[PDB]
Amino acid sequence: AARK
Amino acid sequence: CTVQVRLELGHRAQLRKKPTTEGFTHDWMVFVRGPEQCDIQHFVEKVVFWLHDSFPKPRRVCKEPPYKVEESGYAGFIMPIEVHFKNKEEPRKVCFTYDLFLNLEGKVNHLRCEKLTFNNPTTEFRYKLLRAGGVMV
Image 1 (cartoon, chains in turn brown, green):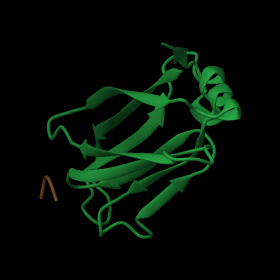
Image 2 (cartoon, chains in turn purple, yellow; image 1 turned 180 degrees about the vertical axis):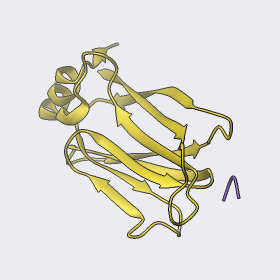
Image 3 (cartoon, one colour; image 1 turned 30 degrees about the horizontal axis):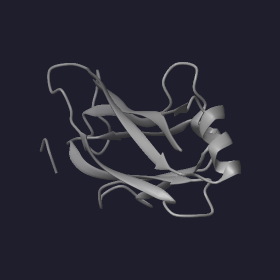
């Protein structure tokens, strides 16, 4: 997802 | 009398050769340390890393060095870190907002220095500071  | 001591917050994150059962693409470690030749254990009671929802038991606490957290994951995130002091008077902690950011095409080796400043500390706290590399000004 990259960056939560 | 004012004493200053130095902290290094940092993290490394490498892209896994194969992702995990849960689709975690990276391994990372985040840490709190003194500069070379500085054991902050002398004035640091504990460090608290407030990880994201999705990690089990996300309030991670290190009471002795190394003050680190190693995990696997798929994304970066903003992370409050709290360093609590072996101080019986205020201030007894400090907080930093830390950005655990990932490199999707390789590694990250990140370092960030923070300078703490304590005003007129108690006699036994001023040691812990000077024992940990503190400097008088």
